[PDB]
Amino acid sequence: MVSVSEIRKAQRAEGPATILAIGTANPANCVEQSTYPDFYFKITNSEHKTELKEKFQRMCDKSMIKRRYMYLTEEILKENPNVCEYMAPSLDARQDMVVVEVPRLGKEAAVKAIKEWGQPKSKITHLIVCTTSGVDMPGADYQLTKLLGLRPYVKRYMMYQQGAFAGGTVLRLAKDLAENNKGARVLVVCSEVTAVTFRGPSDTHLDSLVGQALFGDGAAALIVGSDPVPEIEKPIFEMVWTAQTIAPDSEGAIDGHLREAGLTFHLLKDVPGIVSKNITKALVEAFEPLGISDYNSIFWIAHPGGPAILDQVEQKLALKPEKMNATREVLSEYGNMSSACVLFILDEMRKKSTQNGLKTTGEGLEWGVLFGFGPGLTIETVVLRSVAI
Amino acid sequence: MVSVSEIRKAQRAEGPATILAIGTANPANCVEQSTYPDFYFKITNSEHKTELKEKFQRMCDKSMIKRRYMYLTEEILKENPNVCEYMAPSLDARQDMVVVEVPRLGKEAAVKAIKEWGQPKSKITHLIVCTTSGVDMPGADYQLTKLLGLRPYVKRYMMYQQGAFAGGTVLRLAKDLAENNKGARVLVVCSEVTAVTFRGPSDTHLDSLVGQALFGDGAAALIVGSDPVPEIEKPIFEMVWTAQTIAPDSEGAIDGHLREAGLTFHLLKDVPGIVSKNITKALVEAFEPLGISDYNSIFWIAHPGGPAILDQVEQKLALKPEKMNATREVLSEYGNMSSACVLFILDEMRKKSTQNGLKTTGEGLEWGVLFGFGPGLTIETVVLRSVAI
Ligand SMILES: CC(C)(COP(=O)(O)OP(=O)(O)OC[C@H]1O[C@@H](n2cnc3c(N)ncnc32)[C@H](O)[C@@H]1OP(=O)(O)O)[C@@H](O)C(=O)NCCC(=O)NCCSC(=O)CC(=O)O
Ligand SMILES: CC(C)(COP(=O)(O)OP(=O)(O)OC[C@H]1O[C@@H](n2cnc3c(N)ncnc32)[C@H](O)[C@@H]1OP(=O)(O)O)[C@@H](O)C(=O)NCCC(=O)NCCSC(=O)CC(=O)O
């Protein structure tokens, strides 16, 4: 009797998944980078490690980060000496921080996105939450449903322990949820808190130390939907095509293990080298089908894992220095916020484009690319189209 | 110049997401339930806790589980006393087990699904991995990509710390990935290992104790795609509609926290009561639009969190005793395997339907329902259509 073909035709959306609102938030504690080496070596009781402190000073001076926002404060760190050690049992304390802070910070960003969107939160049909900081059951998706008062029947996607490429992963996921479901409006929240990875310095673990110069906190929220209601909703960017891949010869480039001493990273190859070496193949896969091969002709969003990734990509491709302006401005004012970074960069780009009277939200250009980089080594690619004005 | 409308039309699939292959696997160690109370109280050094052992005997006798498969053995447990205690620092040891066992067991199930499917593994475009046992970076999705030799550009969805409703969550996700992307073939793997939750008994934590009578290990893998190639591929079930909701008055019904002592569950209400009280609303949302209100007329798959959930649902709705046969057979022969359970039940159902000469893979019936239950309290609903023969 019942036709599945008819149900399927009626159930799906028609146009491209579109970003309709972006909102961000960060912990209130602003930590200057200029003074961080002194602060970090003093709070971890490592002032005697003179040569290591000099190496960390050089890491901070080359970071290209001016400041970062951290949930962790001097007072919290003084109450948690095992978090200040390089390797001490401390997961319970870290989890107690981040199981609450991830959804709290995500809530602030989401409220800002929902206000911009301007439509009832009862129209949110799907919720994607993403974090690399802590895990719990029910997860941060259930907590944000409760905190925001979303409908209990919101369809949830809890992306845990994902890593820094997952701002691209949540976009890749939201595209399919919005496009295959008529009326669907997806709230996307990436919320990342360094309390799980902060730890003291050790001279035989310099890969862990460079994370202490770069990682910062923040959350970003999006509303994503297909078939925007003209003039009620306001498109910012459209998603057109996505990919994910594992770079060859990158085994163990970025490992991260969640243990009794928290989350510890381990770096085993040359991340800037691997990303630079494999970015062109990612661009030809995305843009050869669209007939574009001039990579200065598109707008750019790249996860700023560190400044060397950006510099080597710019050099490899001969990007004009300005292509990475929005990326570098986020790195400078917030540091590497893992999965959220790329979403802050989208917000900076559209805000500066609009503020400065450019013709599109993608710096006056039509087509754009967003890249996430992280453990695997994984590269996430999202092809975007800007919107006029 | 470029038309996004044309790209979107060309990029999407046309028909309903279809399950094209199912494969399962379990650890080799088969643990009888009849003797488990003696084994478990002896291995955890709790033989002196006489009244608690009697309560556990009653839990096991009412479980309706005949046997379970466990990665954990007597030899492993004897090497890990802190895993045998109710609450001892042990996450590092547990993580070391499950970061390897989750992908190993998932690989076995996936190979079986890929063999059934019969098509090149190079046609797998998307991979969803789901587990509640351990987390790592790169995740179990990267490990399975490597173990199976999938293409490096497979698009991955790593669902961590999800909980027992997530066999429904992976179906909900795979439906959108398959339906919105022409040609997409999704490998879905749920792989669940009790090494993260096993722990000794405590008479002030009886909610943790009932998990020790019920939780078992296993993995299940699916191939999901839209637009199956007639007679090359072989549809088993079609997905038509999905939902997820949070039952009212269920705050803290099933909490699970991942700590330095591993994953510990905490039960605070009446799960069978909450599920039974809210299942009818879930069924009317799913089936009122299809015009069906006789819930014996559809085929059933329900997460067997415990036998009381099943009994109270059967009683509430006046299901014939046979509706839950496939569900109860899985509970009996494997116990509660968290997210994988529901996928084992789909395999049992289609195998028994085919074996016994019924007309469809859904026990001779056309429409069916699959439910996942877990932390939140969350209910996942997936509406399925069977396939002839
Ligand atoms: C660290 C940088 C900002 C510095 O770049 P520069 O080229 O400008 O600078 P430089 O060599 O003069 O100083 C950088 C400092 O890094 C340190 N350093 C140098 N060699 C290194 C090595 N192989 N192992 C670890 N750290 C190293 C030294 O202290 C050195 O200063 P000196 O030797 O002179 O004292 C850049 O390397 C960077 O962007 N790398 C980031 C690549 C990446 O892995 N980031 C991904 C996320 S981090 C990660 O850890 C993820 C995670 O854990 O999940
Ligand atoms: C445990 C059962 C198999 C037993 O059911 P019966 O009705 O047949 O039996 P019964 O009362 O005679 O014995 C069941 C035993 O459960 C124990 N028991 C009874 N009262 C309980 C309570 N409120 N707290 C905890 N456990 C309880 C007692 O030992 C009792 O035996 P006696 O008192 O006579 O010694 C059933 O309750 C069940 O299916 N519950 C499962 C509901 C659910 O929560 N499962 C979700 C996953 S578990 C979870 O823990 C998830 C997780 O942690 O993530």
Image (cartoon, coloured by chain):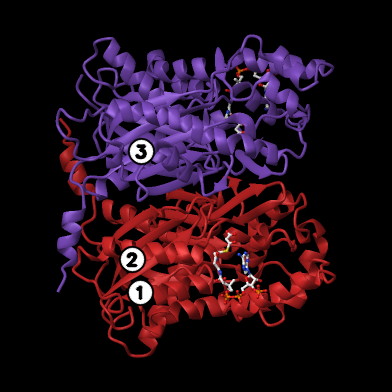
Chain colours: A red, B purple
Q: Amino acid at mark 3?
A: Leu
Q: Viewer-proximal residue, B255 or A348?
A: A348
Q: Quick one: which residue is furthest to the bottom in this view?
A: A357
Q: Residue A175 in the image: x percent, y percent? A: 32, 57
Query: Residue B54 at what x, y percent from top left?
Result: 74, 14
Chain under label 3? B
Q: Tell me the subunit letter for badge 1.
A: A
Q: CA distance from mark 1 to mark 2?
A: 8 Å
Question: Quick one: label 2, few (<14), some, or many (20+) residues within 10 Å?
Answer: some
Q: Secondary structure at mark 3?
A: strand
Which of the two residues, B233 or B142, is positioned nearer the viewer here? Answer: B142
User: Which amino acid type corresponds to the residue marked 1 in the rendered image?
Assistant: Leu
Q: Which quadrant of the figure has residue B208? A: top right
Q: CA distance from mark 3 to mark 1?
A: 35 Å
Query: Residue B120: x percent and y percent?
Result: 27, 35
**Secondary structure at numbered mark 1:** helix
Q: CA distance from mark 3 to mark 2?
A: 28 Å
Residue B64 visible in the displayed image:
no
On the image, numbered disc 1 is attached to which residue?
A317
Marks 1,2: beta carbons within 8 A:
yes
- The quadrant of the rendered image in which ligand 1 is seen is bottom right
User: Which label was assigned to residue B187?
Assistant: 3
Location of the N terminus of chain A by quadrant is top left
Crowdedness of circle 1 by 10 Å Cα count: few (<14), some, many (20+)? some
Residue pictured at 45% horizontal, 49% vertical? A157
Which amino acid is tagged 2?
Answer: Thr
Tell me residue A342's x, y (percent). Answer: 45, 68
- Residue A280's tag is 2
Tell me the subunit letter for badge 2: A
Image quarter of residue B189: top left
Q: Are marks 3 and 2 on the same chain?
A: no
